[PDB]
Amino acid sequence: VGVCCGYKLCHPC
Image (tube, rainbow, N blue to C red; front, side):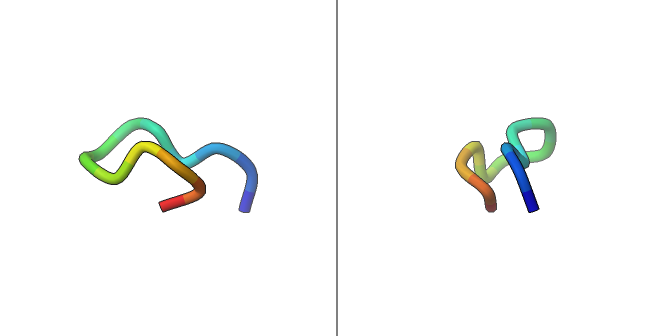
């Protein structure tokens, strides 16, 4: 999943 910081949930979402 990697870093999912580009929506709202900046984590691996």
